[PDB]
Length: 293
Ligand SMILES: Cn1ccnc1CCO[C@H](c1cc2nccc(C(=O)O)c2[nH]1)c1ccccc1Cl
Ligand SMILES: [Mn+2]
Image (tube, helix red, strand yellow):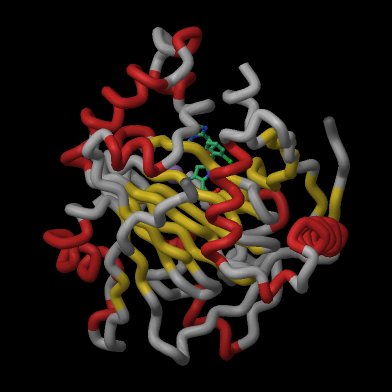
């Protein structure tokens, strides 16, 4: 049987008034969004920050990802441009059609088939170990390292600029993700059970799955039961390097799971102790940071 898509997580389209303060808005949506673990936030139509990374010098060596590495129980340097050419060529060749014509439901169905396939070994690459300190943030930042036009200053000062989120807990910079088709991140929660906010600067959508915090123990129970026994006794911080699991398996065991396709220009917020995972539909560029309330 083919993959059954989970129900859609909440999507919010705040007015310009509601968009004034992120923490205030997230606090207001909390009664609903914390019951779904993840939610999507569409900024007002005219809110479009520029892309502010140093594209000329952007170079990275992505990690290699074997989709079926659990069921089965190298390095290339790219620029942003050459990675995008590799990514589009991979997807268009795999589906035998232009990249933008591949339905999101098909990539989703094919991704989870490949994760459990023993007869087909598909290998992709993910630019996932990129700090915003290396080549700059995707958002404009008034740090003097790169020019900012007057029309872009409001985005350098915006509270939705991930560089302006509060990160100090009572008793940290954004990270970048250059994705291709089938590149993925497995089930995990954040350190200190922190919130996280994620912005897709451009490219094809990023598909998400989320579990509300009230079902965190249920997920971890299903994991220890079905995860490889060799990795059963591993600490959570190490096990969550390989906590790959089909969302339908969690749903069969009574774990509530919600999905969304995060498109370019949209935010995804993960709530405290909300397990989440996902994959990229194609060539895209995301920025993420953990924040405190
Ligand atoms: C936290 N965590 C757990 C295990 N390892 C880590 C550290 C590297 O975390 C990344 C990661 C976390 C994340 N959260 C939201 C969105 C994305 C995205 O890619 O858009 C994310 N990517 C990661 C974890 C597991 C497997 C692969 C990768 Cl790339
Ligand atoms: Mn995360």
